[PDB]
Amino acid sequence: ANQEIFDKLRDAIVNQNVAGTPELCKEALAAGVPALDIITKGLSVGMKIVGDKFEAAEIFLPQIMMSGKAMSNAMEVLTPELEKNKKEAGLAITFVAEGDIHDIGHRLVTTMLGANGFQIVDLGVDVLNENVVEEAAKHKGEKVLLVGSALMTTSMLGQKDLMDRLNEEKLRDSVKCMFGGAPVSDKWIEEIGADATAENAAEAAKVALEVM
Ligand SMILES: [Mg+2]
């Protein structure tokens, strides 16, 4: 059910309706629809279409910026809804690779983690690999999970360096590492030496738990 409001949410993103997206999130929300379904069956569906349109040179950067802001505004209404049911499996240090400012997915995963029994340490975006290493050092010995984002190949490559720097500082084996984004493949995860990855907030939370 709810297909109509899903399409409206999907279209609000596709048509750069920044002001409207929030209203619809409330409309759907008030209709007893779960925040995560609003994202995965509506907003995310639209963001994907907008992604294809761009890669096909149909739309451009002015449209992508507005679709981005459209979803960020939507997240301001759903995040609090997601932080409910705060079901401490450990400490998660979240960040987006250096030179990368894409934070929608990063913010979504960080919200789920924590909502699923995790203490959060959000480093923000454009985080240097050393500041992540410095953060991991301050928490050496305890239950630590490094959650990293990167939506650009150029920034995703730096994840290798990160893993390499964690070893040079013999800090690795004491922490679990999960990278994500999209340019991140199940191949690249082992090429460097990570412990996992997810494709969405939902799975991210599950994998985070399983990886103990
Ligand atoms: Mg810089």
Image (tube, helix red, strand yellow):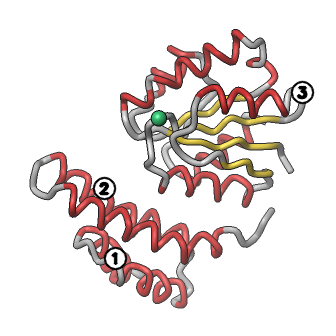
Q: CA distance from mark 3 to mark 1?
A: 44 Å
Q: Quadrant of residue 129?
A: top right
Q: Residue at x 80, y 62 (%)?
A: 87
Q: Residue at x 65, y 44 (%)?
A: 94
Q: Position of residue 96 (x, y in %)?
A: 53, 41
What x and y, as percent, mark residue 155?
43, 31
Q: Secondary structure at mark 1?
A: loop
Q: Which residue is mark 1?
A: 18
User: Which residue matches tag 2?
Assistant: 48
Q: Of 76 and 26, which appears nearest the observer?
A: 76
Is disc 2 in contact with disc 1, using a CB cutoff of under 8 Å?
A: no
Would residue 155 be found to the left or right of residue 66 on screen?
A: right
Neighbour tally class for label 1: few under 14, some 14-19, many 20 plus, Cα within 10 Å: many
On the rendered structure, is 195 left or right of 66? Answer: right
Per the image, the residue denoted by label 3 is: 141
Give, as a three-letter code, the residue at label 1: Val
Most extreme residue toward the top is: 168
Q: Which quadrant, please, contains the C terminus?
A: top right
Instruction: Tell me if residue 49 comes above or below residue 20 in the rendering.
Output: above
On the image, the x and y values in percent for residue 95 come to 60, 42
* Three-letter residue code for mark 2: Lys
Query: Which mark is first along the chain, 1 or 3?
Result: 1
The vertical placement of 166 against 38, above or below, is: above
